[PDB]
């Protein structure tokens, strides 16, 4: 049984596929390119 205390400072723009942030939204979108049409396996809980 572990506790939270996991995660320090999280940007308002993060990826759900792998888990990455960006200084801007535009950038984030570009990244998704690696996921788009690339073994897209969405999570179960959200
Ligand atoms: Zn990603």
Image (cartoon, helix red, strand yellow):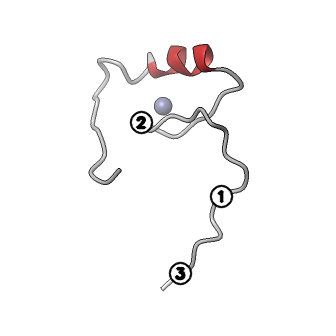
Q: Residue beneath label 1, please?
A: 7
Using the numbered discs, state the Cα–Cα distance from disc 3 to disc 2 in whole angstroms: 24 Å
Which of the marked residues, 1 or 2, is nearer the chain's N terminus?
1
Q: Is mark 3 within 8 Å of ligand 1?
A: no
Image coords of residue 8 (percent x, y): 72, 55
- Residue 38 position within the rendered picture, expressed as x and y whole percent measured from the top left: 32, 22
Q: Residue at the spot x=58%, y=36% of the render?
A: 20
The residue identified by callout 3 is: 2
Q: Earlier in the sequence, mark 1 or mark 3?
A: 3
Q: Is mark 2 within 8 Å of ligand 1?
A: yes
Residue 3 quadrant: bottom right
Identify the residue at the far bottom of this view: 1
Numbered tag placed on residue 17 in the rendering: 2
Q: Regarding mark 3 in the picture, which secondary structure is present there?
A: loop
Real-space Cα separation, disc 1 to disc 3, in angstroms? 14 Å
Q: Is residue 3 left or right of residue 10?
A: left
The residue located at (58%, 72%) in the rendering is 4
């Amino acid at each position: 049984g572990s506790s939270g205390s996991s995660g320090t400072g999280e940007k308002p723009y993060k990826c759900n596929e792998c888990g990455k942030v960006f200084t801007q939204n535009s950038h984030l979108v570009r990244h998704r390119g690696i996921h788009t049409g690339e073994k897209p396996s969405g999570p179960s809980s959200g």
